[PDB]
Structures are given as structure tokens and as C-alpha cells.
Image 1 (cartoon, rainbow over the protein chains, first blue to last red):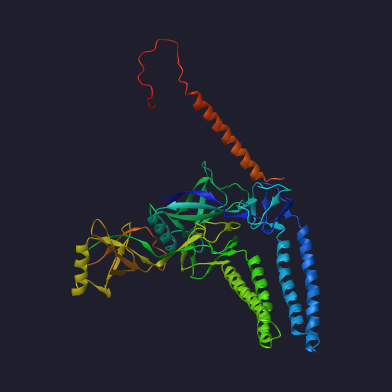
Image 2 (image 1 turned 135 degrees about the vertical axis):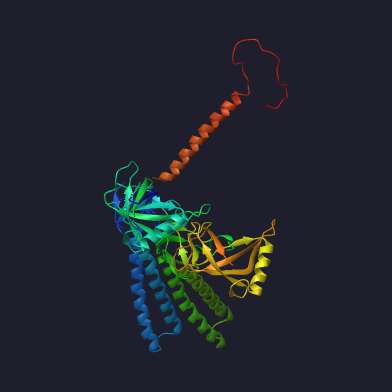
Length: 237
Length: 233
Length: 53
């Protein structure tokens, strides 16, 4: 007849990432709506930059001053007008200031806490006015990418190598390199409109069984699909 | 005929762990893919570690010329031994600081210890990690050469070892015999391996011996934890 | 925001378990007086004084 392998498996986020502060300070602003969608590099919080701005302004000012003096003493020591010691001191101060600009520049950059990935942000563990710390145990927020979404399918090792063969023999239709065109039956019984992809590289092998988990990727442009849903994937042979 | 049952095992396994504290900026592998020994799997944010390293190097530049200089000066008695000893102490401290800052910066690139297939990441981006933490971030298993692992009574083994010796048994190499492999679904592996008669473990209670066969696995057909049969004559 | 949301949540949770722990302890202490369930005629005591119950 028609050859049908329906496959049990769970939805999973494509990518998950935490949002953490990397400088100490007060949360001046949140900038995002809880539950909403966010883009990689999107600013999610503003940490109070006043002290960071001023450390940076000051580090630049020390560099300028100190750099000019070492230029000046470079010439002076040339005409034996100063001793090596005074030039040494003048250069030491300069090298030190040059190095100090970097950390101040870095800290200032960290006052804008950016989304590490594009996706769906949850609740904020933190409140405007609250002090955060670099290295603090809890994340301020979590972003989950959902637009491509994963469907984790486990199977016996024979079953998988069976399927793999069917793709090489063309018995089975390709959806790209090392992948099969695949369809999705939801939790109830209805169909997914969009159609996916079953990649045949194993992601894990169970210790007790020889059981293998592979993944499917489906488009999900409206979050019809969310993590945790128990679905069934369809193959045509 | 002769069909010794087996279980497939990875040829080599490794854990991926952070050796410096910081936050995961990037995961650089696809879960399930092949990676090489030395390949970068994660990026710990290195901005500060890079800044510390460059401060340290700057500081070492100053304290080092100062120390080389005071060395000449004490020789001229233009400076005391205390002054020179202090310049030399500050130098030595700078050198130590450079070395340690280098090491930390180097560890911001979490590498794969071996070539093999990598699984899932136990850790997401934006997670904090710690040198010496309990949990591995990922595991890598070399699958291509794959092991089979046959546990047999010790009579079996010494029977087999004289058969190779006489010739009743096709020779792969020294201490090794040509073998073939039958999958859990009766199918027949195209490739053929070696049954290596160098003993790997001997069971405690039962006197039974585990030996391993090695099969090529260049397509990734075989995975660990398969029930199979090796095949001799 | 003189403390964090997490700190307040922690102090709130500590208070709740501790509220529960006092209730358990109050009950336990109340039950050291073993009371008659119904009015009536009581037989032999199947347990001696100094028994472990």
C-alpha cells in the first residue's frame, strides 16, 4: 500500500540563551516587554552608565596627557636632556594609561545588556532600581528561539539505520543534505501546514536501550508550536 | 559460522570542560556533528581576560627595563642593592602576572580534546561556568573506527588463539583475526574488522574474557550500544 | 528595591516553611496528651507505662 512511519517525539527550542549583566550597577531601564519577541543584539536593559562614562572619560584624559608626556620625554632623552629614569617613569605612566582605557571601554560597553539570540523572552527576574552584580548566580532573563523549532524523535538503532538506507536508495525523499522531507501530526490529530526536515545525525544514544534520538526541524512563524508538545512525525515511503 | 555476540562501543571518549571562570558567549558547534581534536567548541567571553593580559604585558615592559637598568646602576654604585632587589622583585612579579593572564586568556577557547562526534551541549549560551565545576559541558565520541567487544569463556579464547596460530583462522594481523559483523536485524555489515586477541578485561566471578574487534565505520552506520554478532570460521 | 526580588522571595519562602514547621510542632505536642475519641467504657491498657509507642 502506502508506507507510513509515524514517529513520536517532543518539541524543543531551537536555541536557548541567558541574559546576564557583566558589570555591577543599578537597572535604570528594562526596554523589553515580558513574553515578547526580541532580536539578537537588541538592548534588553540599561545599567546606570554614569560612573562608567566618567571612568571612560577619565581614562581617555589620562592617556592623552600621559602619551604627550612620553612623546615629549622621548625627544628630551634623545638630546640627553632627561635621564633614562625620567623617561622610564614617563613611559610607564603611558603604558599603564593605554591599558586602563580598554577596561573602561569594556565596562561602558557592558552597560547595555544585549539579547544574545533572537527569540521569545520570558519574565524579568529583576526590577528597575535593583542593583545587579557581575557573576551573580541567577540570570535576569531567558530567550528561546522558536521560529525554527525542534522535534526530538527517539527510535531503536535498527529503525534509524533502516530509514538512513531508504534515503541513500532514494526509496525516501530528501529535504537537504542527509535529511528527509517530513510531516507533522499535532497533539490532537490535525496536520501542520508547513512541512519539515528529519536530520539523520544522532544527537544522543540511550545508555539502557541502544535507543537513538534524532531531530526534526519545522518552521514556526506563528508560534503554533511550543516546547513540550507531544507530537507525531510522518514519513512517506 | 561461529557467531560471538557483542555490543558496539565508542573507540575513544572525551569530556569538554571549562578551565577558567566566565560566561558562555558562543557555542560554536552544531549538536550531533563531527569535531576535530583542538577544535574550538565554545567561546568564554574573553574581553576582560584580554584586557588583564595587556595590562600585565605593559607592566612587565616597564618593570623589566627598570630592573635591567638598576642592574647596571648598582654595578656603578649609583643605586643600592635594596633598590635593585626591589626593581628585580617587581619585575619577577610582573612576569608571573603575564604568565597567569596568558593561561586564562588561552582557556577562553574551550577546545575538543579529541576528534569524534559531539552530542548535545549541557550548557547554554549566557550560562556561567567555573574552573573545576562538577559537570562536563559536552562529550565527544570517536565512532569511526568502532569497537565491538566480545566477552567469552577463557577456553574459547585459547581455542581461538591456537587456531590463529595453526591457521584454522584467517589472519588480520599479529594477535588479530579477520571478522565480519551481523546487525541486530540480521543484516550484514559490508565492512569487516579485526578481532584483537590482546585481552582487555577478565571477569572476576566467571573467568570470562572481554576482547574487542575494531570495525571501520566511515559512513556513520554503527552507533554505540548495538547488539551484534562477530563472525569467524 | 533595597533588596532583590529573589532575596525577598527567599525570605518569604523561609517564613512559609517555618510557619508550617510550627504548626507541625504544635500538633505533635498536642498529641502527647492521648485523648478519648468517644465517651464510654475503657478496657485493659494493651500498652504499659514506659512503653515505646
